[PDB]
Amino acid sequence: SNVRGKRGKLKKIQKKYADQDETERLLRLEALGTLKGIEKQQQRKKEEIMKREVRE
Amino acid sequence: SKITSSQVREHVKELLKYSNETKKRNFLETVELQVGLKNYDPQRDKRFSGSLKLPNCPRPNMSICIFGDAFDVDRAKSCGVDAMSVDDLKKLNKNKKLIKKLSKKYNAFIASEVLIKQVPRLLGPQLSKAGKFPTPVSHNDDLYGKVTDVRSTIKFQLKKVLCLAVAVGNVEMEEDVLVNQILMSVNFFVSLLKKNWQNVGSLVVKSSMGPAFRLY
Amino acid sequence: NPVDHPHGGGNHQHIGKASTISRGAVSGQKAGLIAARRTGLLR
Amino acid sequence: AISKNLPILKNHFRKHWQERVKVHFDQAGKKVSRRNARATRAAKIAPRPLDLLRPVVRAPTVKYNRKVRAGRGFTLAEVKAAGLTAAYARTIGIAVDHRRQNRNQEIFDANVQRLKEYQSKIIVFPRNGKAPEAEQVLSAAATFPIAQPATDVEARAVQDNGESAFRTLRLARSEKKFRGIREKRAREKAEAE
Amino acid sequence: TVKTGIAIGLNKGKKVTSMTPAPKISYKKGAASNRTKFVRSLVREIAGLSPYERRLIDLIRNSGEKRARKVAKKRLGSFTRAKAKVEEMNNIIAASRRH
Amino acid sequence: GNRKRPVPKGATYGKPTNQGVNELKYQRSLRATAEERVGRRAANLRVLNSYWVNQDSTYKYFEVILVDPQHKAIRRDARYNWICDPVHKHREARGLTATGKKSRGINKGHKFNNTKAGRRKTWKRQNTLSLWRYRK
Amino acid sequence: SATYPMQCSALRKNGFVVIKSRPCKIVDMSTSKTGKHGHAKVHLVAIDIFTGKKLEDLSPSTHNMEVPVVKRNEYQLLDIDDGFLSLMNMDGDTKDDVKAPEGELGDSLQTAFDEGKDLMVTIISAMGEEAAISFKEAARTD
RNA sequence: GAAGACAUUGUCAGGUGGGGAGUUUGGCUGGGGCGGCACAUCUGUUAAACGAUAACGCAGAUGUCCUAAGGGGGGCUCAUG
RNA sequence: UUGACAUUGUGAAGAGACAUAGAGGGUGUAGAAUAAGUGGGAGCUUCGGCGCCAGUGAAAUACCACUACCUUUAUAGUUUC
RNA sequence: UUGACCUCAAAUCAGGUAGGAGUACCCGCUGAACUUAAGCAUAUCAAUAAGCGGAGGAAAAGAAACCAACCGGGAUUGC
Ligand SMILES: [Mg+2]
Ligand SMILES: [Mg+2]
């Protein structure tokens, strides 16, 4: 919402993915490889916390 | 400059009127400039740091320690300023409680060019954490002159908080001197600041045990 | 021949640049795999 | 291209200038036909003098205001002072200009006098009857010439009183130059409490 | 406004005796007549206000005549028309307050 | 809107100063082309004037006044029989109406030195080379 | 000036260039004749010093490429706090403007400062942006 | 029936755009190309004991450095053995 | 292709951002306590009490102000989504 | 039910009018490049050639929302 560029994404989702189901969305996202990227970012965040712990 | 000299003269006049006549205090009152900067980010933008030496001293009597060699300690006997030698620093033996006690004892430190290398090795990084780090002095220069200089130093460093404060001078000085010093300090601050006179959030003049007065 | 197609020409029969073409490409450029999300034979 | 010590020429002949070349071979024949047109017009308006009466009037700019010349037509104020209406003056052969004004009494008096002499000199025929034929002249401008006014007499007495006529011009230019700054200083002096 | 007689200065030019001619009727083209004043007042009563005039009324009520003149200068062509428009809208505010 | 340059696929075949296609503007007005189409529709009439009535994003709307030069009420009535003179055929096509003279620039003044008696007429007049019998 | 021009053939390996307004350091240079008659073209493969990205370019050999001024400077650490190093210059000058490194260099430097070595830091300046590249330990003057 | 003040349309503005347009792509040179710079300069020599004097002749150099390594004065004498 | 303005009217809700009027708020551990930070400060006192030396803690405490971040009400408010 | 009004039609209805030609000159639209710059892209050629629409014996313009700054001039056109 407040964060920039969210609105541009919203228009697209409404435009082409309105007639879709969650099962289809998950399958499509995996084929695209978008899902893997999200996972990698989450993993990095865990890594940052891990580094602090190791130092301690 | 958005701030005008006549407005500075006026605000200094009621400031000294309150400090001197109406409610006098036994301790000598230092005049403070408290600034806050606007539309600025400590994390991304460059962290400005700078220093200026005022002509008339703000704090004549503030405690200063001189880390020094044999020549520096022998000169410091003539200067009358407290000093501990390299042997004394080795006798301290990196004990945190005593060096924290020294850091809260002395506001300012002056060190020799030779020993400024191993001042971190004998003492550690808690001086940089406090923000009191020793200033270099050489054999050629006068120690008491640089004590007067450090006592007249004004430093602006960004750090993390977007608000700074310095001590312009005493209440007891003359009005034109106080006006000139506060004007040159504001000019030095905006010279260090990028996009000058527009990233100035607020400028506040105050005296010790005194109310705030707002200059823009 | 290179006058007739983007893929034409050369001393060997080869495409030259990548055959995946942008959706924002113009007429005369869209020759190949238009707006391909992925290529190749999946297993 | 550029060559020996010659002046820099600017000959504008880089268009198809030979498509637009007007050589006036018909100067003599055009003059002959112009005289033929004047004669047939005079025969067509056989008593009337081939041109209207024009006023005397002062030429506009500072280069030419020393001279006086002919105008388009008389002012309505001038023809009312002459004592005839504008429509009647236009019918009896007086050019009337509705859009020039009278700001100069000498020019006004000269034009009124010129109208008085024209009304004295013309003969106006009755609209119906006898038509007493009267042997036209062809130029009202030649019968009423434009005369430059005599500005002064040719001999006078010297009247000198010590201003040299150069100090006067210089002081006038200086006070025009420093006019507005003096009222600015006067205004701030007045509003200085 | 008489001339000085010399060729330069403030009132340069030759002194000639003036005439002060009769005023032309075309010099009074923009003069307001009673009948057109009555017509303009009646059609203003009938038609009311345009949207930019309404938001100007709000700008004199809230943000003052300086912001009102800035917006009217952006809306109309020139600063002169903006000043006249803000003046007549202030007159409408005074008249409606009297109403 | 504008006048798109009618070239195939935007190719102009010339110097880059003439490569513009989109932002080019027609030199006559929409009022002028409106009354010219009305005159072509009724060629037996004569266009007198036109005025704006309405508009939207797509169209501009004009009303055109036309006078019949064969009707006896205009053959008589000397205030209007000047339109029956054959020099007034297609005034809107020659630019002789009010918006036609506005678009041609026909006005008195120093702001109209290029277009005062006709732009091409003045151009010929000041690009003519005048040679006399006795050369000056 | 901050940057100065140079010729492509005058450039050689382990030198700094400006590619797409980035300070880059060359790893590969290759020249191939354009046509038999024509001049050779220089292909340049370089690595950005700050970001580590690989940027390449092909130019005529006679063409002039922009070259930055890179200064490497030697300092001693004072403290590492909030991701900003505090350094100490010869003659006693101090700067805190340098941000700490974010990679394995930054991790190794953080562990070395935590376990208490005296660390010698090399920071480079090129085109108005500042970073730290390497650290050593002072073998003498302990 | 559907859709609905959103599309569409008009005008500006940013991006993309060899699909297309226009144009350019140095010189010297024991042919041109590659190489080099003899393309703006400086020292010695070729150079023929005034001056001038060529070659892609020979041996080299320049696109800097210096608040003193500038200016004035005083004292002293250097390399080497 | 993206944005603005016009075409373009009629109605309801819900969020967000500014102006200027005022309120309250900050708990790893250790430390007498709930430490948002800075900067001054050795005396301020209204209690003759609180700080200061001293304890602990990265950061120290009275007495002053400033600046963020939060929550918080209101305007014939200004507005955006 | 009848008679109006408004708007829109139909007639081999009564009477008219337009088209096409010519185009030297005239009034507009549209619109280049060769060339010159000793290269070339703005510029120039040129507000031209080619293309399109519309007149007359001339056309167009024309009786100031003008020029001026003077002691002011006074529709347009042409030299
Ligand atoms: Mg190929
Ligand atoms: Mg169009």
Image (cartoon, coloured by chain):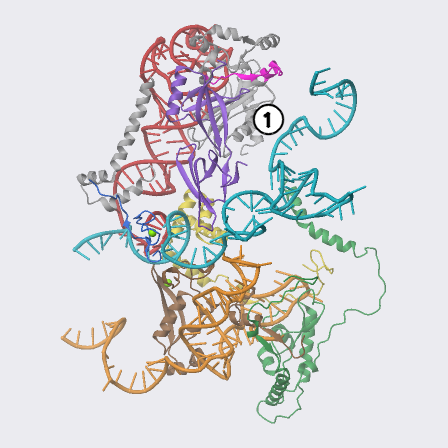
Chain colours: C blue, D green, E yellow, F brown, G purple, H cyan, I red, J orange
Q: Label 1 marks which chain's residue?
A: B
| Image point (27%, 34%), residue name | A38
Please name the amino acid that badge 1 sits on.
Asn
Residue E93 can be seen in this image? yes
Judge by depth and name the residue closer to the eye, H16 or F85.
H16
Judge by depth and name the residue closer to the eye, F80 or D18.
D18
Q: Quadrant of residue G57?
A: top left
Give the image location of residue B47, x and y in percent: 47, 28
The image quadrant where one finds the N terminus of chain E is bottom right
Give the image location of residue B143, x and y in percent: 60, 14
Asked whether mark 1 and ligand 2 are closer than 8 Å, the reply comes as: no
Does residue G93 appear to the left or right of G135 in the view shown? right
Give the image location of residue J61, x and y in percent: 52, 72
Does residue B46 appear to the left or right of D150 in the view shown? left
Regarding mark 1 in the picture, which secondary structure is present there?
A: helix
Q: Quadrant of residue H75?
A: top right
Decide whether residue B144 is among the magenta residues. Answer: yes
Residue E97 can be seen in this image? no
**In the rendered view, would you say G59 is above or below B148?**
below
Give the image location of residue I38, x and y in percent: 45, 20
**In the rendered view, would you say G115 is above or below A27?**
above
The single residue placed furthest to the right in the displayed view is D157
Q: Which residue is mark 1?
A: B180
Judge by depth and name the residue closer to the eye, E7 or F109.
F109
Q: What span is colored magenta in the figure?
A: B130-148
**In the rendered view, would you say D125 is above or below E27?**
below
